[PDB]
Image (cartoon, rainbow over all chains, first blue to last red; front, side, top):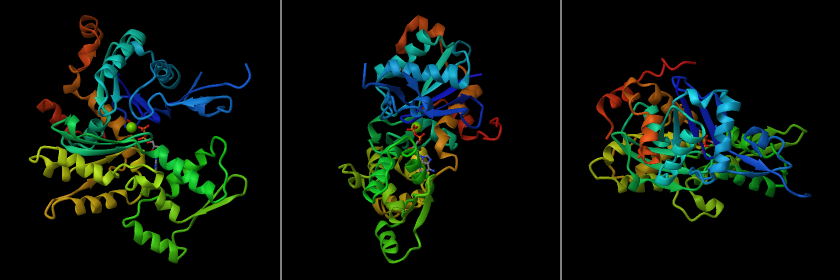
Amino acid sequence: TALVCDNGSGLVKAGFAGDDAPRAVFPSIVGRPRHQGSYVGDEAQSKRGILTLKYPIEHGIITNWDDMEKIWHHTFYNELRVAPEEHPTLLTEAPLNPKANREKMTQIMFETFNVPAMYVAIQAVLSLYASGRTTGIVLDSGDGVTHNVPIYEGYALPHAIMRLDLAGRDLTDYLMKILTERGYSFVTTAEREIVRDIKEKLCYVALDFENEMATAASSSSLEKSYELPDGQVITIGNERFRCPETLFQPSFIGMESAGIHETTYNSIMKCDIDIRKDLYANNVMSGGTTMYPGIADRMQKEITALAPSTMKIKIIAPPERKYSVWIGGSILASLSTFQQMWITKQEYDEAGPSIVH
Amino acid sequence: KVAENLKSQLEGFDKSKLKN
Ligand SMILES: Nc1ncnc2c1ncn2[C@@H]1O[C@H](COP(=O)(O)OP(=O)(O)O)[C@@H](O)[C@H]1O
Ligand SMILES: [Mg+2]
């Protein structure tokens, strides 16, 4: 049985092909000490007070291979409890992953973990597959990175890919900051995980930011309360929608980038004029940070205002978005027609890292 | 451009069949 490992900028989602959900999900964090002369995932977040935390995949691309090798080891042995030697392994990569990087992942899988076969697929493409499409444009917003990825007949169009270094983790930090400014304190681990939970539970995307501000200014109807496990009650109203509003207005956190509606449109306009109508009718959202209530409606509205007045625009937000990359891998790796697409260790031993391309 | 039978399997896949 093949393995599916989605190497997330914030969370590893790993599991077995043909399953409907990952078995393991844990932070892609490696932690170490230092104040008076290595751990992974949860036990790195857990007792971290004696740890400096690092993201080896901070923005979707793997930048530290020793730490990544630790993550993968944790994944195989500690989370899935499998012998890597026994399972074909499908790995995910970010859009615009450099060739040497994909070569490096391939070598590690064969020469370190001795997998019998492997494959590397683009996350956004897997999400599109998961929704039953091979043409469309994906907005993938995860933990450390957001991409727009137009895909035609199963192929991501590299020159049209957009990247925004703003996603779930930044929205968490932003909510923390604005709550801190109001006088609340979050120093520990959960706090700050409590702030993450507040974000997930109470935040939403306004259909019209200014109108929602007016509503929050003139009534108490958007106020919501969250109880902290010591007695503190934090109440928030406009911060519920101001926080994810950052995705559409990155200036909220001092970033000069265009927002996710503008990058979606710019991505489409980089594509062959002949496929744009198919991209506009197939905007698929994926990733945890697209889970906000209202985000599809807002994207429908913003893309409509940017696109030609006639254009048919559809946003598809699958209920399972949060794991659709992983699920796309699960489907892909179980398909009969995929089984000769595996790179075998024999194919590898005969040609080296360059086979993946 | 992905092979045709693969596209067909992807586009027509029935997400039941996925083990719980
Ligand atoms: N219901 C939710 N609402 C808003 N954000 C969410 C929700 N669920 C998860 N997230 C956010 O999604 C991010 C992780 O999503 P994911 O797609 O796994 O990231 P990655 O693949 O980059 O690791 C986290 O920041 C998490 O807070
Ligand atoms: Mg992801």
